[PDB]
Amino acid sequence: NRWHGAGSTADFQKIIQERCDTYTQTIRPGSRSRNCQAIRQAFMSAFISKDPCKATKEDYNSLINLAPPTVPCGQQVFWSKTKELAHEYAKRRRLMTLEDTLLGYLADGLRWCGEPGSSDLNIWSCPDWRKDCRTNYLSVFWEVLSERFAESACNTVRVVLNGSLENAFDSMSIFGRVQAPNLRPQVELEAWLVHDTGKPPSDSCSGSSIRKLKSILDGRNVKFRCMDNLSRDQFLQR
Amino acid sequence: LNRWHGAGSTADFQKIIQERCDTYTQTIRPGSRSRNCQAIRQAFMSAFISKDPCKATKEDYNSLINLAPPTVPCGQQVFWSKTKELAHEYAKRRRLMTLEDTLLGYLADGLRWCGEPGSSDLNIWSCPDWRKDCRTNYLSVFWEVLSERFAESACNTVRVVLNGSLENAFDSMSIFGRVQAPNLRPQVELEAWLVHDTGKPPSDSCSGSSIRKLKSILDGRNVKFRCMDNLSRDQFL
Ligand SMILES: NC(=O)c1ccc[n+]([C@@H]2O[C@H](COP(=O)([O-])OP(=O)(O)OC[C@H]3O[C@@H](n4cnc5c(N)ncnc54)[C@H](O)[C@@H]3O)[C@@H](O)[C@H]2F)c1
Ligand SMILES: *[C@@H]1O[C@H](CO)[C@@H](O[C@@H]2O[C@H](CO)[C@@H](O)[C@H](O)[C@H]2NC(C)=O)[C@H](O)[C@H]1NC(C)=O
Ligand SMILES: *[C@@H]1O[C@H](CO)[C@@H](O[C@@H]2O[C@H](CO)[C@@H](O)[C@H](O)[C@H]2NC(C)=O)[C@H](O)[C@H]1NC(C)=O
Figure 1 (cartoon, rainbow over the protein chains, first blue to last red):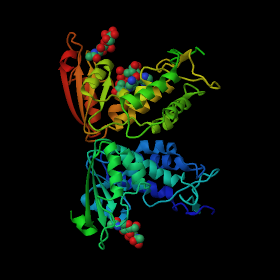
Figure 2: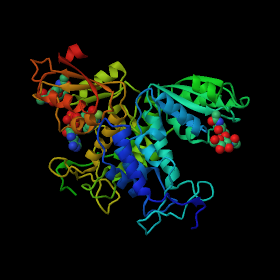
Figure 3: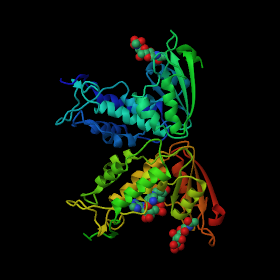
């Protein structure tokens, strides 16, 4: 197919419904009950048969309202450029990243796109964010989910950043661009800049990029505590 | 066209929306960054103009709510039902926030609006009454959409000001009842303040039908509940 991105995950619909069952029954049973058939149907309806490069935030409002990415106060974890580590940290400390919310869990690691005049997914290729269009259903999903995740944050939240990069805070990242500026006001944020096993840090809490982050948080009336110069192992020990 | 049961659209609706948006974003609650009030007003108009006033859906307000979500800091939220004036004077004095203190709630408070298919203008003549005409009207749908997100957004300790004075301080069919209470997140703690007129005595209290009503809803959602009754209008304020 013509897009520069990999095609939709095979059997997407089955995966998201089975993941929904597993999540609602065995991961976060609670609660209030949710219909996973309805959630799957809402997920498909958001993007199926639509122009794969005209995704808007508004296409996802209904899906999100069925299961907002809300995490109990003091359990929320943000991350940027630290995928593996942040999730290991969350899993071990019993915390929740975006990928641990119902909708994040459904979509984590999946790919999807549709095609006008078709009720099927495009399993051949999907729009690439850089080569094709930013406004694609995969990228917009994560942007909008990220935004609501940031909005619903409460009490103490933590963020895991990459101390082996020149700028641990990337203002063009999803964290920098969508999450930090939408963080609920008056929450408290603790940041951990963590470096490879490995090697001396390339960024710190005193670096320019973190000062940029503090400036955004000052604006959101968010108290900020930053810790750095820790290796992955040292971090996971504290 | 004057066929509906409800008062027509507020005259100057568009001007009023723009003025209030400027006031809110510049003088009341300046944000950490700017919101484009022209864009907000355009989105508000586009939601309903030239549409069947009885075919409103929540989706019609997606763009608008995305421009200005009615969310606020934990512990800040004041809910109300049948206690508008009291609740708002309460909120003001304690520097808390009702829905009407959010950007969109502030824009829309006390206004009416509806359109008519094939017309680019508001219907100044009449608009659908939510009882006598249709529930799916742009005025009722707006408040339900806003109310739901505001309730969703609540965290830590939040409060609701009830009246009674009424045989049922908690009306299960009010917006608070259908839409707010049932959308509070688990572990949120709701304080209910049953305030009678003062005024001769009450009519309802933290014991009654109406509450086993509310409390029941909170239970089963995992919302903690504190009910303070036997309070007057002067005590409370
Ligand atoms: N500012 C407002 O006009 C407003 C309207 C509706 C709802 N709210 C939000 O919900 C709560 C109050 O609504 P309520 O229905 O619990 O309280 P009432 O005093 O019973 O009603 C307030 C106004 O809403 C109207 N109302 C109630 N149900 C509907 C409906 N289904 N459709 C249109 N209007 C309705 C009602 O007639 C009254 O003028 C309050 O916490 C606030 F957050 C605000
Ligand atoms: C900080 O960022 C770097 C760059 O992304 C990460 O290193 C990559 O990690 C992946 C996943 O293990 C490897 O497959 C790549 O080979 C690595 N790329 C490079 C350029 O080294 C690193 O894991 C991050 N560090 C922390 C502490 O999260
Ligand atoms: C409880 O409900 C009653 C009835 O709505 C409220 O009384 C009204 O208040 C307004 C504003 O002062 C008056 O103009 C109306 O005449 C009143 N209506 C009736 C039927 O009395 C009363 O304000 C509410 N009490 C509290 C504590 O909010």
